[PDB]
Amino acid sequence: MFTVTVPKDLYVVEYGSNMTIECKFPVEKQLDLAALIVYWEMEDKNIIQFVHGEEDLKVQHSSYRQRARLLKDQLSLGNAALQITDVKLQDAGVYRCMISYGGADYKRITVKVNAPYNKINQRILVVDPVTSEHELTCQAEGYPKAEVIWTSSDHQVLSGKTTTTNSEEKLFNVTSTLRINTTTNEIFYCTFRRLENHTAELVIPE
């Protein structure tokens, strides 16, 4: 019998990275491309229409002409791999692969797009060197909204101001400002807690 397998049914890819999702099917010896058909679909869009040797670029949807392709070299291994480049949030969802090869079967695959706050840009502004008054800043992009937790070197917790906007856009820009009098050699921490957490360390200079 002919069974399409998705040994990996859940993909968690990071925003902006490349994605390659796979469907396995039985190939007992030399693959015959003339008897092979491969469909890749998402929602109501056709991504790959690989029929009898060649991709039909006419049926395939316009949003994927340049982003998506089927790794042909893999097919001889009984592996139908769809590659999509620079993944966005609207690439998350359900994909269907249909393999026909002397028998037909299809499977579904879930793709999750993760946009974490793990690139934290920090700023240390000296407002008043007399009183050692500083204005610390932590900023990051990610989805969804997140809150920022400021902690001292004794992991005390302090209050700061936080602003959240939108931008790549439909992503969230989160920036927090902490005004505080310090002690050089002191270490502060900004922690981005998303709705786990990533923390940037801010060392006050001499």
Image (cartoon, grey):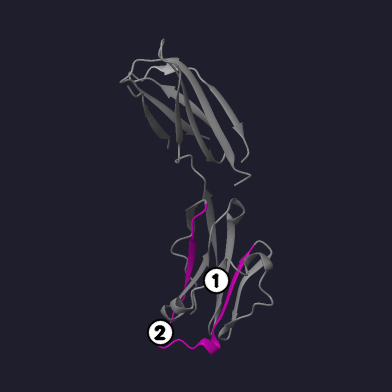
Question: Whole-percent x and y of residue 89?
Answer: 59, 51
The quarter of the picture where residue 124 lies is top left
The numbered mark at residue 69 is: 1
Q: Is residue 100 above or below residue 68?
A: below
Number of numbered markers: 2
The numbered mark at residue 28 is: 2
Residue 46 visible in the picture: yes
Residue 145 visible in the picture: no
Q: Is residue 142 above or below residue 54?
A: above
| Residue 49 counted in the magenta span | no
Q: Residue at x 54, y 58 (%)?
A: 86
Q: Residue at x 51, y 37 (%)?
A: 140
Q: Identify the mark nearer the N-term, 1 or 2.
A: 2
Inspect the image, locate mark 1, and give the three-letter code of the amino acid beneath it. Arg
| In front: label 1 or label 2 | 1
- As rendered, which of 194 and 128 lies closer to the eye? 128
Q: As drawn, which residue projects farthest toward the left?
A: 185
- As rendered, which of 77 and 87 lies closer to the eye? 87
Q: Which residues are magenta?
A: 16-42
